[PDB]
Length: 48
Length: 67
Image (cartoon, rainbow over all chains, first blue to last red; front, side, top):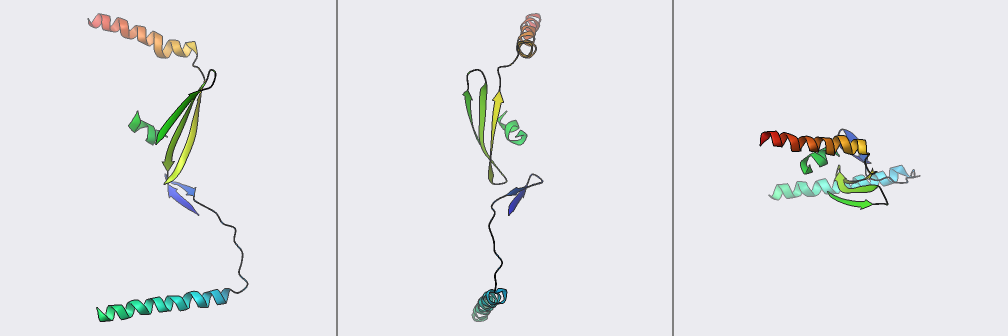
């Protein structure tokens, strides 16, 4: 991943990755979390 | 380098190996740092001639005419 100044890219860091064997499971987890997050702000806005 | 220098003409360090002068810049670019080193050998006496002396003679005599 990099940084763009002076009309040129300038790389910041770089990571060794690996494909997960269970994409759908991390996906459920992330999005359950996200659902929770939105709902919270919803309730807060109501009270406000 | 130009954008850095023209204002000043970031931090700099200089060192002279036996004959050559070595100039080091500590700065940053794109947020990220940028390091470069200048490696300037002792300049030539034609270069010395043309860049300093003959022009500097020229200075001296022209200001004499001024006076």
